[PDB]
Image (cartoon, coloured by chain):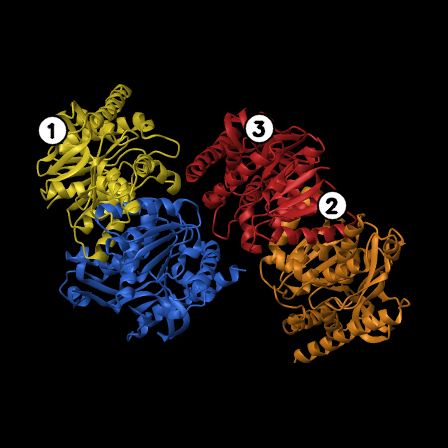
Chain colours: A yellow, B blue, C red, D orange
């Protein structure tokens, strides 16, 4: 009975649709502006479903009114960046697209939970909130689960441990101003600081890893000639799951801050829980230095958001 | 310990890599000729693995010698057809690529099981056997599972039943001369003929379905502007699973015929079992009319396979 | 002292090299990507040169840096079309190869005059310009002279006259949208219209001839099982000769239009003079109907050129 | 009015046709067994002719009766050798083809002058003579001009001189047993021995050059992946020109020996004159050691000719 609407049928959207089918999360509605594309991917997904013994319904469509009564909305519509570009270079063209999608969600399914993925991520979440007229808890963006996966992955490789239970908090905008928190990094519970004391990893090695984490999105673009699609989709699917199954998992994602971390009235990457009712920020006690870094990331997001609202007229 | 080598890091390869990681089938070796592309898709797949709690090793490489000691080899290297083209139009350019891959497999990992996917499928399997010097049971091509999934999917939709236990045999080349067998179609055990007698489906509706099955590959190209990727990858994975886990499953795939179905010395789509030791054809009793249709399909594959050998000089 | 560089040592390239030797136009540099092939053709051309008393230098090579200081560059690198394909089907694969050649010319001999021949012709000239960073007058493609030779050859046969002094103008893309101009067709000075008045040829016979001219490239592929090689080489050589000897001959060839024939910023088949300084378009007064046809051909070339730029990412 | 018939429309045939058109030697009849091929090349050659201002008639045909009243016949029909093969490996298949062509010439144009080019060359000239029923002076083969070109070309390179007036005699079969004669090698008149005395070239360098001349045919095959086409065609054209124009030039070619060089009743590579009346051998005074080498070459050609006649039943 659950309806999952993918607004954008590109790489990310299709794989999200594929992952949703694998766990039987819901019926799919594959929407795109370009005719034929969602219908074709829907056909390929049905044949996939038939081989793997999944039976959920899959509808490829160019009529955005088919998004009606979606329980979940994943928004990937928009352009992606190429080599040499920053995420922020998409601000002009994607803001306009995000506004249009916001206006459509507003009239067709105002009760949905909305996961935004168009870049630049934090900014585009703010745009969606402005024109959608949905409650702020019902809107979020994925990024932090992606950036955390890259940072944990690298930490795991340097410590010669499984990535499976390397956990971390990354605060701030999905960009060059991310703030990975060493204090809030653990390896199956054990703080990262223990592994520095045991000489298994050095402060310099960690700064190196933080740098690779920041650039990773660009590095994949450079190597693969396309932007990361599998990891983003997995992250998204994890956030859909936490909503549908009322799991109340504690992630980083772009969420409405409201007095938390000295910030108010802005969607930005932060610690949050996701459950039945949406995405709910949680404030943890930062050090002065940590908070100072975070606030600096928050300032860019503020600026670039305003820039976006301006460029939309 | 199992090594799975994906020769070709395009759409199909990457998704196959994805599905192998989801079931922990083995460590991945992502190979492509184009520099950077495998390394980037490996990075994205690592991050995907970290988020889903899979821990297998993933290596993106341009050095084909990294394929050494692969247990499994999936070949997608080659060009894909565009709108208006037939699969057979690729014969010239893909034959040459398949030969080169054959030669590399020959010197680097002669003990592997080899699933060919490059088009036109049956033809390219015959090229790979010629220049690879591997036993014929250790080589096959995936197609029948994809064509079957399409046909069964359509049968299921018309009968208002789950596709989950709709099974069927499609013989012949992956092309316009497929031979779907009504007699060998069942719905959780019940032959298709019972549903015609019960007036739940008509002989004309079935012929319509057979036509859509034949043209499906082209239809997806037309709609999606790219060829099918998810369903092919799922089919491939199913054949990998049947080899690794010695399952002895009965599929249709491009296999070496040797006195079966009045055919010898040719890889062509047929009923086969896959296990530990490779792909083994099985002959079932066809009617005169069925065999005639099958022989006709076999003839095209014969011709076009000769053409492919000729055009390689 | 003149250096002629043949980028591509297939049929066309070799014959061009053979014709250049016959007229002592210059030293040859025979380049190809495939090892051994240019070296072997260079050997054969040396022996040919020894028998016919020509003494120019011939170098066969796989090192593209040997192209340095070439005065002339002929580009035939790329794939040729088979039976049932259009020239436009090669867009994907040849665009990439053309870009790579462009980049090489850019760093190794930026002062050369460049004759492009890879199909689809007009499109590939535009690709070369884009990535080569040469002046537009220093770049052209051969086509018109070939299409004109066909059309004139057929006119001559129907009129029972020597083809030697039948001249004509064909405008537009090297493809189905060619625009042969009856008004600009003469037999040793006498307009074609005089032969219609004298009943030596009819308007219908002319439309038939225009059709055969359009399909000629395909008809040869069908009959000979390979694309035309001698006539393309002779056309090329004639454009080389007009550059080297500052002849200022008036041909049709793919040339940079810049306000001519209501068209700007595109290489397309048009009336042009070749001399010391390159290829220079010349506008002649067309009727409304003629111009309409020409603009229609220009539109395809526009579209397909965009398509080509798009498919290169 | 002169009719030149090319029996075989492959590489060599077509280039011969092209060179004959360039010097206006005659109307062409392009014959091949394979339908469509000669018709297509004939179209290409007509368009070539139109661009270069040549007006001779060009007929592509599959009806061998069109060879009637040819003044000249060039025979390239047959298979060529690939890498690793010797010329002598074609003995079986080409002998039979040659016989068939002999039988056709016999009934359709018994007054022609016949230049054989199919390999192995000398052997196949003996076959043509046996079944054609033409006078022996009317039949020859080209080889010695090709081998002489290669040898003179390498001599010229080593001496840093123009190849233009380096002349030489090579006697014997077109194969490993050629006998290049140093004594009959001159550089614009000056014997090669004067350049050894002046230390400009050494006896070892000359033996090296003689080896490369022998293997040259195979070396081009290896490098170009096809057998030499341009130089052969030029050599052929030269013999055609010496017959048509009654030049009485002194070449080496496969000619009927009749007491010359202790050899009788065999076509083998030797010094000959070509004029209006055909190919006429000429005996020069050899040393013992020269004649011994030449006799040894003549013995292989004997053996292999007998072998060819035997294999024809």
Q: Are marks 1 and 3 on the same chain?
A: no
**B159 left or right of C65?**
left
Q: Which mark is residue A135?
A: 1
Q: Please report the residue visible at 26 percent of the width from the left and 29 percent of the height from the top.
A: A97
Mark 1 chain? A
Identify the image quadrant of residue A305: top left
Task: Name the spot of residue B81 as percent of width and height, x first.
Answer: 40, 50
Q: Nearer the viewer, residue D131 or D253?
A: D253
Mark 2 chain? C
Identify the image quadrant of residue D79: bottom right
Q: Which mark is residue C22?
A: 2
Mark 2 neighbour density, 10 Å: few (under 14) some (14–19) many (20 or more): some
Residue that carries the numbered disc 3 in the rendered image: C135
Mark 1 neighbour density, 10 Å: few (under 14) some (14–19) many (20 or more): few
Q: Please report the residue visible at 30 percent of the width from the left and 54 percent of the height from the top.
A: B233
Q: Which label sits in the foreground, 3 or 2?
A: 3
Element at badge 1? loop
Mark 3 neighbour density, 10 Å: few (under 14) some (14–19) many (20 or more): some
């Amino acid at each position: 009975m659950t309806k999952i609407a993918l607004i954008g049928s590109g790489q990310i959207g299709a794989i999200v649709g594929e992952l949703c089918l694998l766990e039987n999360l819901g019926d799919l509605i594959l929407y795109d502006v370009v005719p034929g594309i969602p219908q074709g991917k829907a056909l390929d997904l049905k044949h996939f479903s038939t081989i793997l013994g999944v039976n959920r319904n899959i509808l490829g469509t160019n009529q955005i009114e088919d998004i009606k009564d979606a329980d979940i909305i994943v928004i990937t519509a928009g352009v992606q960046r190429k080599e040499g570009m920053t995420r922020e270079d998409l601000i002009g063209v994607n803001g306009k697209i995000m506004k249009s999608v916001a206006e459509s969600v507003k009239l067709h399914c105002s009760k949905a939970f909305v996961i935004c993925v168009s870049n630049p991520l934090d900014i585009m979440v703010n745009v969606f909130h402005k024109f959608s007229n949905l409650p702020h808890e019902k809107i979020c963006g994925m990024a932090g689960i992606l950036d955390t996966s890259r940072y944990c992955s690298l930490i795991a490789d340097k410590l010669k441990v499984s990535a499976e239970d390397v956990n971390a908090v990354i605060l701030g905008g999905h960009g060059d101003l991310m703030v990975p928190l060493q204090r809030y990094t653990s390896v199956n519970g054990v703080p990262l600081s223990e592994f520095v004391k045991k000489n298994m990893i050095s402060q310099n090695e960690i700064q190196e890893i933080i740098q690779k984490t920041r650039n990773m999105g660009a590095e994949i673009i450079k190597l693969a000639k396309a932007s990361a699609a599998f990891a983003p989709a997995a992250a998204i699917t994890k956030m859909i799951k936490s909503y549908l199954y009322n799991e109340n998992n504690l992630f980083t994602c772009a969420v409405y801050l409201n007095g938390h971390y000295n910030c108010s009235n802005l969607f930005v990457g932060s610690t949050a829980k996701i459950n039945n009712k949406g995405a709910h920020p949680v404030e943890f006690p930062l050090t002065k230095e940590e908070q100072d870094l975070y606030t600096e990331s928050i300032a860019s997001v503020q600026s670039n958001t305003q820039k976006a609202f301006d460029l939309i007229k």
